[PDB]
Image (tube, rainbow over all chains, first blue to last red; front, side, top):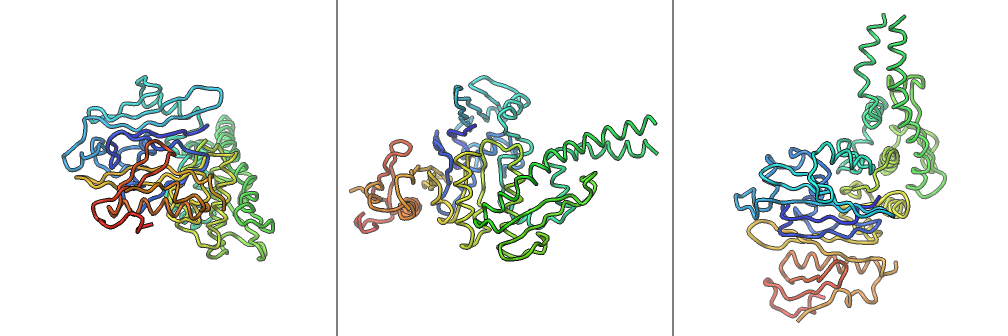
Length: 348
Length: 60
């Protein structure tokens, strides 16, 4: 489970053929204000199956360098990912732009999207759910969800909400053969929900403890309806350091932040992808905790997941083993290139 | 003339070394320097760029 490197050719501002990485276990992507970093985020999304409409273009061809202003650099472009795994040969996943359409490839054999996605699924990478990705502003959105919105989110990640339409259909079909028909869909939804929820609830205290580095902090997740949790809100109670037990809602500022982070990291600790792309989470952080989150990432990256962070704040990315620095080269169109820098060669 | 990022970082710690690296990126963006890295994680070499015709070690 390791993203070893990304290879790009003529994708957005990445003109020519360029290697991105190799990545270490904790790598920060940084650079002065430009399109380079977000184009790299898009390259990662693109190689993992993202739809064109989520890539800030109208047509696939517009992803070829220079294509937006009618000066394409080639008739094709590609992004590939090298995925490494102890005991096994490297597997290369590539998506090529060919004739305005996507061609998917595993180790240079052309495949259809269904097989590309199935193969990524076997590796822990859920391209439709985007389990590997923490989008920008993800912390803020979590911190705003009330108990019922929290239940909505668990129905999504656990895919139990898929069964939510049949649950209601068989509930009307009830009011002897319908008693068994409903109790079966009730049980499928419940086992899906609880398998996810109970993992998150189990892991959340250790995460909340790790983020606010002292052991005095505690966190708890309980359904409102412990029988059918999908039919009610999910309660989230925190004992912030020094303060008494309270609902996460009743928190405030930099501590509600750390509690939403712990819930966010806890949600992802279930069926976790082998790598974790964090797009500018250090943006919603104060000099009161950004260092602690960065230390939490550093600690988790030596064992639990590979961390790839796009970061604006030195107090975050100086904790990385490795920096990928994005810079512009002047040209007709914006051109981006990268540098690699090993930080482990220096003390702190 | 030229300047090696790795020599610039010799007696630095992590946070100072990152800042020098970051400044290579900034100075390149302003076209104060040109940049060269032979291969990943090799030294990075700064060359004079078009929008600065002073001395190179003045920037550093």
